[PDB]
Length: 147
Length: 50
Length: 49
Image (cartoon, rainbow over all chains, first blue to last red; front, side, top):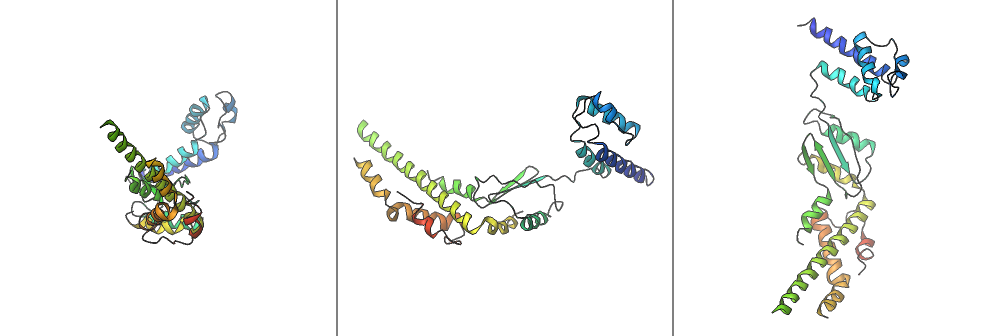
């Protein structure tokens, strides 16, 4: 219970640290190439998993696996990946303001701000599988329906 | 009768073309206005429902 | 000939293009604020024919 929780958390943190440190160690390098690149900066299970990942050479998103390590401590589900698209490139202040503003769900959810300048002066915010569209291109089509 | 139907179809097509041209002009004007003023003013609308 | 006459009449901005564009900018593009922070030159120059 309590002992397991601290143990699980410590193991997750260690795994995340190993993945972040040794992700680029065997990154891209093939099974024979990354075998030497495989350092002692991993547990034997972690070293075996890194060897399996770099046997094909797909050891690029291991940092995401590192990001997968801490969330698995708390059963994840905090991704809440949202995507914001606006016609003008977002300034850092307003970007942070709208990042904070979508706190109704989980707070500063994973947001990958996009531009797509085909839009005119609006917001397309997709949280999970619900999209909100107040872009003036949407209003443009909603008026252009007169055709 | 066929000539009258063709005239009606031509009138409808002309109305559709006028609507499309008006939409394109409105889009260009809105784009110019957004470039001048700045789209940041629309950010406050993000709290309308989200 | 009738379609050409209608197109010539609609080519003028003050007849169809300018008024419709201004109405769309005011009621649709904005919340009853056509001026925004400019667009004075875009009302006429961008209208063209």
